[PDB]
Image (cartoon, rainbow, N blue to C red; front, side, top):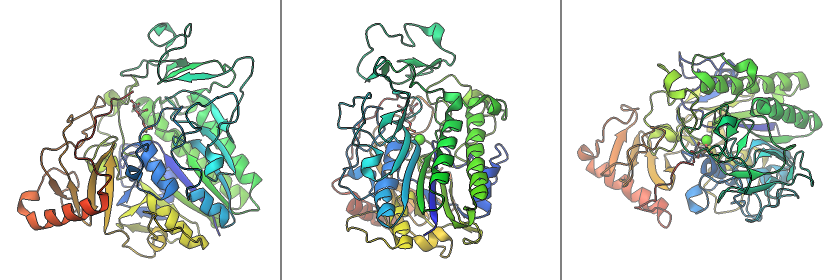
Length: 485
Ligand SMILES: O=S(=O)(O)OC[C@H]1O[C@@H](O)[C@H](O)[C@@H](O)[C@H]1O
Ligand SMILES: [Ca+2]
């Protein structure tokens, strides 16, 4: 029973840490988990977007088995059943105090959230004893903190209303009042304005509750330190959802100019500082040697994701997906293949593993560690030994997902079905919409340059058979292209 901390960054690409040898960014605090722990070269989220990757981590279920597991608005209902087995529920029944701090994006309420009372079901009802959260994303209304289902700084004399349907009569928008903007929108992100930054969706009221983006990193770090100190004498499971480098990239003043890459780079150094502050505080509390730390990212990277923040102009030679094709929103490997480090000081011996592992496996793997009785019916597989770096093999195969489109990794091979859709979305990311069943040897062709399906017809038919069996009932040959907000 060590403490367990799952740290998720938000769109942090395979090439957005220096752990794998990048010359174009420096993430020393994050790299210390990688070098001093298990550094996974073949670590995966299930999905190339937030809500589905986070759903798979929390439930141990493939998210494409839930029709609601896609990018959620801030007023979306909770997509996990109140009765369903979850990572925090398991840890709690095995003697842990549970906390979720930072990004949520799994939904809250039952479709008519009153932001002025306790919002249920939420984190509390899926097994987090403590929560202090962003409902959806830092670019989505409501721009407030939700602590155990209550909006921080709410006020009956300035009540909060949210709509993703239309503006509140009388309320300024990015379009009505462009003079109020300190950051320009590039596409979407042109509804309500908060702290000079235009957002997705419309918000009225709660002047007191409205967050300040530049102090968000510090506010969650302080909630994390409060949680650790409150529970230092107990076994705790903390889910720490960093907002960086998700748009808007408005990091604290002290991080501005730390990089050559504008707000995007500066937000990554902000996240690295949060990780450094966590490690420092664990050392201070004397907990480092009894705390298992898992660091990862919900999905692959993106430069321009809706704001004129200089990300494409100032990227220079920086390859955020570190040589992988695509990125956020892509069915190519850069969508799901993310940094993944597992660290336990004095227990795990430093290792670089090529084991095919997925965030979805943490529920069954941690379950094995703490002696859980798992229900039947989870996708989550027990690979505890691979996660501890004791064994260098885990999965033979993994399904990957990009906004409802599915593909297949099996050993050194990726099979992508063909899908009708755009080559790129407005971000410039390649979506992985190909015209034929394609096959990539990712041992030799890391960057998925070449569809070699033609010279491997036997292997292709087999990978198609296995993919159809695992996805039947969920796989859709035609998937609606969801517009960026
Ligand atoms: O990391 S995620 O939460 O999946 O990102 C969600 C994205 O949704 C898109 O509609 C917006 O254009 C992006 O700016 C971003 O907010
Ligand atoms: Ca994300």
